Length: 155
Length: 48
Image (cartoon, rainbow over all chains, first blue to last red):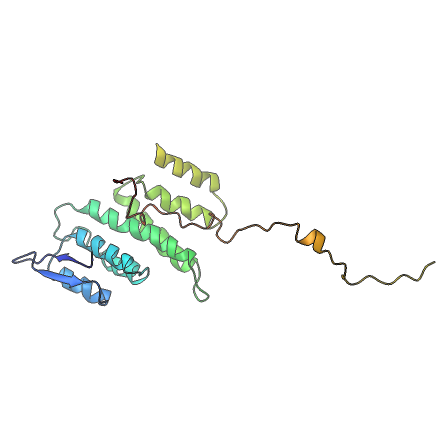
């Protein structure tokens, strides 16, 4: 909401980060990971940053959440594929709001490489096919292929 | 022959042929919407 819970290792469910202020996302990675906190909270505060009106620190703090797929999590690799599909969609989304200085490929490279690790564990997600289908419209080709992978979503 | 002016210039103008044209909207090739299944964090399908 404006402050959701960050669980501890010992006497958990005690600490909070109020999102009305804007802390730096890298110390958030720390204060999460000295606590061996579950991967779900990383998505939750990523959504908090996004609803805070942030698209770039939001998408780069989760890059630090790509390291901790199953760190102490007892098979939350489903949570890591959910993590990584967010970057596989929002790298290619933030490439469309490109600026005068970088290239589109300056985000498409990271989107495409991380999608490859996204397909190492899980195949044909409701967002896996979206990432490559929206990958096609950027280049003006594989357009019926993009339509087919979207129709793979309906089936 | 007649000494015709070289009509290198428009003063009529072509504005009858100009404002008759209705102009396309191609700002974003997927028609001005970010296409995403993640940013619908909300849904009106809930009551109500």
